[PDB]
Amino acid sequence: MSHMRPAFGAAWNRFKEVNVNVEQVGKLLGGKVQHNIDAGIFKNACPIRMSYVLNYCGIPVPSNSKYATVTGSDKKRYMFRVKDMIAFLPTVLGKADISVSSPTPAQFAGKQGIIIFTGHGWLDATGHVTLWNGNICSDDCHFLNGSFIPTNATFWSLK
């Protein structure tokens, strides 16, 4: 069985709607998301953005012990840890079309879809989830960052 995936256009459009800095993202999504953003408890906009994209493209973020979630003023669930979004994606999209070490844009030429860049900073492993249109990311790509060294890119095509 194949898994349904969001249309690339719709995903790109919702993402555009939330492509601002974290505090502006809270100031937009309202509710407990905004509260935790203003408190300094949520500092990463990335999983919240991606939660908004998935929620409004018809993949509702679940109520599950595997994923840390709060609610926005829309009563929909939002993840706020990037590792959780990263784990969540294959469970709904199926296995990635591409996963490569030492990621460069050449490996994704002529492709469009959801892309996860993982790697490490000076102290911890981390990641970034975004959209890729064949030339740019919807916010920032992390190909071979501040001081973030990318070691993998994992990617699903969207139509």
Image (tube, rainbow, N blue to C red):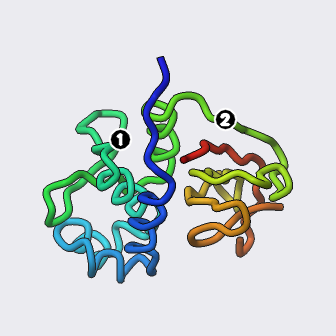
Between discs 2 and 1, the one toward the N terminus? 1
**Residue that sits furthest to the top in the current view:** 1
User: In x, y percent, where is residue 67?
Assistant: 35, 41
**Left or right of 46: which side holds 74?**
left
Callout 2 amino acid: Asp
| Residue 110 seen in the figure | yes
Residue at mark 2: 97
The correct choice, above or below, for 109 with respect to 22 in the image is: above
**Left or right of 86: which side holds 63?**
left
Callout 1 amino acid: Tyr
User: In x, y percent, where is residue 135?
Assistant: 73, 66
SS class of the residue under badge 2? loop
Near mark 1 (Cα within 10 A), the count class, few <14, some 14-19 or many ≥20, is: some
Near mark 2 (Cα within 10 A), the count class, few <14, some 14-19 or many ≥20, is: few
Q: Nearer the viewer, residue 64 or 93?
A: 93
| Residue 11: mark in rendering | none
| Residue 67: mark in rendering | 1
- Disc 2 + disc 1, Cβ < 8 Å: no
* Residue at 62%, 51% in the rendered image: 115
User: In x, y percent, where is residue 153?
Assistant: 71, 48
User: In x, y percent, where is residue 49?
Assistant: 41, 64
Q: Quadrant of residue 95?
A: top right
CA separation, marks 2 and 1?
23 Å
SS class of the residue under badge 1? loop
